[PDB]
Length: 60
Length: 60
Image 1 (tube, rainbow over the protein chains, first blue to last red):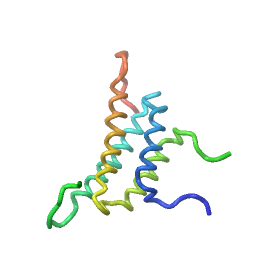
Image 2 (tube, rainbow over the protein chains, first blue to last red):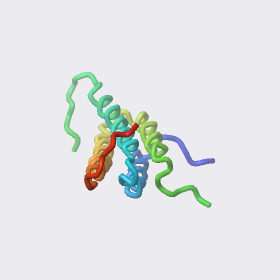
Image 3 (cartoon, rainbow over the protein chains, first blue to last red):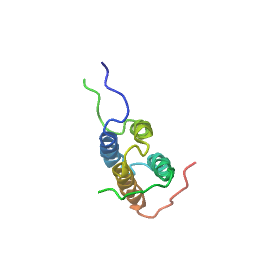
Image 4 (cartoon, chains in turn blue, yellow):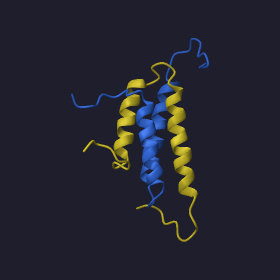
């Protein structure tokens, strides 16, 4: 019943994360949010690259 | 009563984001995720830089 489960459109979390930083926008050296935001993306992109060659068609 | 409010420890958003992503791990060219992921930071890191010189002491 309780709201949860990942893959929540993926954009939902991203949007909420942004709205949060909007308020936490370097309010007091929030570099921590940067390392997190960055680490997520580094791992995110890294996984993207990890894939056997076949076509790699550009997203429409 | 309903759970909300930003800056929820911030990494709380992020954490869930990665977990989400872990699901969307290049599941179907979720390049949109990284676009958001990046946008977040480029907006995040940028604001960080936006600050008058005074000391800029490195985080412990």
